[PDB]
Image: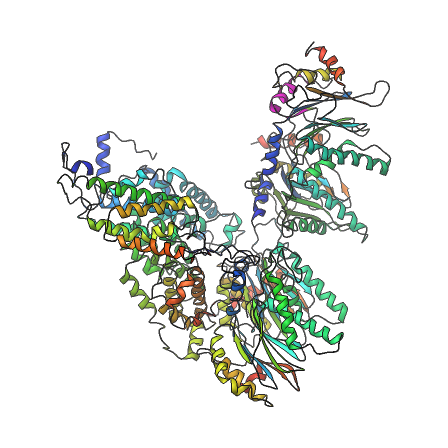
Amino acid sequence: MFLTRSEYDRGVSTFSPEGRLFQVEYSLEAIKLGSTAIGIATKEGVVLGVEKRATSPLLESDSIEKIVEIDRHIGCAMSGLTADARSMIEHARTAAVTHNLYYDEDINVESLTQSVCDLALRFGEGASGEERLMSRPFGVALLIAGHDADDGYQLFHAEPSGTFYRYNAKAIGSGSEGAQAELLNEWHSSLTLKEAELLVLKILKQVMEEKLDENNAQLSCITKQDGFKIYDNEKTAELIKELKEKEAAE
Amino acid sequence: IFQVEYALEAVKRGTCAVGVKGKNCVVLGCERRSTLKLQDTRITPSKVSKIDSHVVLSFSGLNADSRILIEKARVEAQSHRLTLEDPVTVEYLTRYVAGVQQRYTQSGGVRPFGVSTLIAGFDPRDDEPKLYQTEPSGIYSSWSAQTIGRNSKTVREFLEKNYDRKEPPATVEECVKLTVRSLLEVVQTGAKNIEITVVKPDSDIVALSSEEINQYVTQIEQEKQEQ
Amino acid sequence: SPEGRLYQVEYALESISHAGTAIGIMASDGIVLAAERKVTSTLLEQDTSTEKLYKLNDKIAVAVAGLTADAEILINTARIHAQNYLKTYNEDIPVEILVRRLSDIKQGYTQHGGLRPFGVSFIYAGYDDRYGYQLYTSNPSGNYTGWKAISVGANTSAAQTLLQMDYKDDMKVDDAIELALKTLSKTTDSSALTYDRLEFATIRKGANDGEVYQKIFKPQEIKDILVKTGIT
Amino acid sequence: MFRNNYDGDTVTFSPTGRLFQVEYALEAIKQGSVTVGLRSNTHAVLVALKRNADELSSYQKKIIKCDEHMGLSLAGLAPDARVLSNYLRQQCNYSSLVFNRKLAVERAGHLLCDKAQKNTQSYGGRPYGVGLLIIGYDKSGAHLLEFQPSGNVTELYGTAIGARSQGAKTYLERTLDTFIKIDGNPDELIKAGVEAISQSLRDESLTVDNLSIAIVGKDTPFTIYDGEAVAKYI
Amino acid sequence: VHNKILSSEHEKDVVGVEFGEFGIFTDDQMTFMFNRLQGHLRTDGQIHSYSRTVKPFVYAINGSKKDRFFEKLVSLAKAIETFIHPSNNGFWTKPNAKFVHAFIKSYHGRVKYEEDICARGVTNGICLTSFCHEEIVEIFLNIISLGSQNKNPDIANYYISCFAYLLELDPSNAYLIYDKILIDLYDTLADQFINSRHRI
Amino acid sequence: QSNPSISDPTTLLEAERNDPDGLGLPLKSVPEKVDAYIKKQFEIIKNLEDSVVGLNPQQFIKTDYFYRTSTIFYWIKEMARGPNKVLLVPYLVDYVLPFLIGLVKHKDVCALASLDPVRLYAGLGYMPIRKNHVAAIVDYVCSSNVALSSNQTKLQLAFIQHFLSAELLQLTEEEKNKILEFVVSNLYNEQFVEVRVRAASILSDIVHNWKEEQPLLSLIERFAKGLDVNKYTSKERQKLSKTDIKIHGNVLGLGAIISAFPYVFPLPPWIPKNLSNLSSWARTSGMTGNAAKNTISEFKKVRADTWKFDRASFNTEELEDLEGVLWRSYYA
């Protein structure tokens, strides 16, 4: 064993000799160390699943809200400090209604996402030019998924750093490095919602190294027609039962 | 930034606090060392704190820290009735309390609270019991029953193996029957150690006294020895 | 705050067990306050200060054990809360409400950890027509507690013991005046107790009716009750 | 080993006369993808190589419109360019409203220099960490500017910033007298901007998703070509 | 045993205590104390006054059967290597320093006691050779050079004071040390370190 | 019952003298009639593996198999603490480590009755092991039955990383190898990408105490044969980088070697020439080309303060070749 250490570790909002901002490079590793969360996009809807991880029969699951509505057409899933994202969501719900008021239309998923990033982009304790009023990078990553009529169904990864990518299917949290390399294998431009409802489970089964039920998984989706609904425990189960069978195929 | 976990420690060390849902009623329970001989008995028996006419709240932690919460809440409880004419819902009172302990970390850089709290009661009109728990982080959870505090783990273990959802303590009387047993495990003398409050549908909150608490302990340890 | 500990607090909570020594005894028909005075020089002007016994309102008073310049900052703002609750509800402020009002400012620093905690620990003696006579305590922890008899400062742990011993619930007021002096027999680093090392106070059932007189003792009145045993 | 005592913040001059915190930022440029810029007497072109995350993700946009006469490309820290590209968008739109005057390119140069400079006087804030190639057609011809986070904005015929910037910076250096004479041809000046950005690739292959191009000048307002629109140049 | 073997009376009733590879120690006895000392400097920091803790290792060297021991010392320096680096301070930076000094005091200690005896005619092949002094410098030179730049000036004065002890052995290596030290110094007087206080 | 109180001092020292390790007797040795009891409690729990033939976390905490198992665990936790360690060792190889890794026996069952197995199994890497016990333990890990477990693999792999740190300098170059040939057989295991990486991060702990230059330079070669040159033309690297495991390993491995020499104060010329072989690959987006960017940023970082100088041993304008390398979402 042995110890590697740079002299510019630690440094808060100051550049390493490379141009790296280690305070924020680390902000980004702690997504890899929270609850699992997975999003997949079809041409027939978008699916978001997470890991519940109930720690008792008492604690009635469902106070475990790791997937929440934003407007009827935009949902997001979160991995990490669920408590630290209360404010991040308030701002997104507030921005989406505010847009609906000022303009009489549902707000573009691309721009709803960018607005949330523009919020965690106010990290600091000393800014001249424009003021960024807050204290620390926002300690939570987001999968934001919804539908507008310009650019079909969409999936987005909002990072604490204030930037984002639009993945066609993404995984974040404890299993991500592995779940991600599995989605990268099993995703095609022609999935059906039924097919992806299930692939999200198969990949939660894998990177949880366990057998799963409605006490440890929550499924949700967002269709053009029905909006953004979160599957109640019954539906999540005969979706699970439906995999126990599909994989007993060969 | 780690100071959160440290505060969560003070939780541990403090007056032990419990709570228990029922078929249609709810109960809390908690406190500390009888009386140091010479202390005034009749002027701080403020174990569980009334928030509205239908909502109560106990805590494990720094007693001097709770008060700042039991107020900011007792207030938003009115400032909701006032700007929306509608008593606060037990989830909302809870989400507001927890949401405050949360904002006592991530801005300005100030210290977080040395309390976990339990929050019980019935929403307005609706007669479905509600029980929640908060902690210095900003996390709120709903429980069929729970405890937080000192030797709280002994109790959470007891309860898990004594409560079942299939059949919740329906009787008003018997729902307390249980909450007592579960603190006798961790106390340090008995009835003289921890007391209880009881809220039933529609703003009917009736806290229990010393004499009703010993028509219980001394009707428990009767059935006990019978082997 | 490592193990669940309030460090900057214990710092000042034990800085208290250094300065001063104060006592409160609640009788059935009165209340009693008392304190020892800091290391005195021959030339310090005894009668003026009233340095560790302050009046808050005509019906409430506190004994101090802590840094003087620090308690004055508190007391100044508590004498005001009293009067705001008058001008507002035209009733005299209830003791618990005043105590809590302070305890809440103490705990204000015990958390907005950008300014330094309070020296000072209080015994409050007050009467309000809701809860008879009252005796309260105020460490910079933020906590307050009810007391039939109490003490703060140096030699604290010691007096609490003699007190526990000679106290009876049926106690009169004069009986409790003694118990207070008597048990500053022990808890005195100065061998032999004088009228000038002292400051005293009473809240009795009035010198006349069914009401409430308040009385911070003048030096002579002390050397008079000291006469009952202490020194003669 | 060799510690540094004068690289703590921006309010601190190294003994040899050096603001280390700025030299470090000037390096964040090279931590992002390569982009190229060049101009004739009648047009200005930009070529950027959008970089992706997975095979499964979109590509980072590297060109942003500023007004109908001016645009820029970024290499480096994204948010820092979102912040600066926005400020530019404002002054442009203020010179339009108050004076009904397209905001000079030579002047947005002067205005960004001063904006970035502010972040190197102040204790607490870090410098800007991105480079910008800015293009436009103003009342005075075609134009190209290089914006380093130090404040130094410099006007050029062509340059390149970022990851392996050096491959193109050396092509353009040799092509000089050839491309600045590509007047009245638009398709041909982009053919050049792309044959230059491709000196800075290894065995790497431009596609419809890799390539991002923008152009402006005389009678062409700033337009951006991503996706299939870029195919004709591959 | 070492003291007694030399010059005086090689006995005390028994020269029936053989030296060899690893002092008076088994192969496994030596092996154990090495991984225990490594345990101390890398994991559990459990040592006090080190002069005492180092003895066994110094007085297990055999001038004519080193090799197998120096093999064990080198891998102990290659382990310890990273923990001396100026920007890896921790619970260990004391133990590694107070040891790398205690060991080179307690080695030079021995050498200057033997060279006092080969001023009495008695070489003994147990004695430390010119080639031990060589492989000692090979080992602790990057180690000593890293420690001396350490952020704590006391923890540095330990690694820096080892140069004097090594040079007294007048090893063939002597130049390697004078070479570093003189560049480091001439650079400093030419202000090539002006950005870094400690190097100067 | 573990105090060894013997008859004579003489009878005693003759037992210590005749021990396998040039060292001594296990101080405190659990007496047979008890070694029997304990062995029973472990093999009574193996009898009941049918008891949870298929139940769930809720119908688990209620079975007898759990109750036993929980008690045994709490016992192990309290043996590994304090003066009882020398008592606990003989049981690891056959009993305590096969157990504990009762964890694919359900991850979520542990979260419930809060038990941290991961933290104990691995915290048993350090401890009072004796010359002969090392043997059987290295043989238990590096198991040819290994292939048995699944992401409890990144567990045995972390137990090794700790053993090594507490049995380094005490491992016979034989053992020091049985380990390294296991670690390396994991940079390649089809299926789990999770572990190919935890393996490489560990292979460096080895190659740090490995200064002898022919064990070393003979790895470097073993790895850089699966990549070197433009074995394949551009279009292909893209395809391979995303799927081929034999090449993920080769680049993870060659990556660890370079990250095992953090500060060689003047830089070894095998590092430039072998980052160069690694740079044409960190230019490919995929799964290996990713963990090859790790290796070049990890490096460019720790070399930071010695860089004023390291620049000069990079004639190769493959200085340029190292500029991409680190990319996160906030860079463009």
Q: How many marks?
A: 0
**Is residue A133 depicted above or below E18 in this figure?**
below
Quadrant of the drawing holding the N terminus of chain D: bottom left
Q: Nearer the viewer, residue F319 or D9?
A: D9
Q: Residue at x 31, y 65 (%)?
A: F219
The image shows residue E75 at horizontal and vertical percentages of 30, 52
For this orientation, the residue located farthest to the top is C232
Q: Nearer the viewer, residue E159 or C210?
A: E159
Task: For residue E109, say whether it is visible.
Answer: yes
**Is residue A50 depicted above or below B64 in this figure?**
below
For this orientation, the residue located farthest to the front is E189
Task: For residue B214, say whether it is visible.
Answer: no
**Is residue D185 depicted above or below B65 in this figure?**
below
The image shows residue C176 at horizontal and vertical percentages of 72, 17
Q: Which residues are magenta?
A: C150-169
Q: Nearer the viewer, residue D232 or A21?
A: A21
Q: Quadrant of residue F263?
A: bottom left
Please state if F56 lies on the left or on the right of D66 as rendered.
left
**Is residue F179 depicted above or below F95 in this figure?**
below
Q: Nearer the viewer, residue F106 or C110?
A: C110
The image shows residue A246 at horizontal and vertical percentages of 52, 69
Q: Residue at x 67, y 49 (%)?
A: B98
Please state if C106 lies on the left or on the right of D79 as rendered.
right
The colour scheme used to paint the residues is: rainbow
Q: Quadrant of residue C110?
A: top right
Per the image, is F126 magenta? no
Please state if C229 lies on the left or on the right of E43 as rendered.
right
Q: Quadrant of residue B199?
A: top right
The image shows residue E18 at horizontal and vertical percentages of 16, 41
Per the image, is C164 magenta? yes
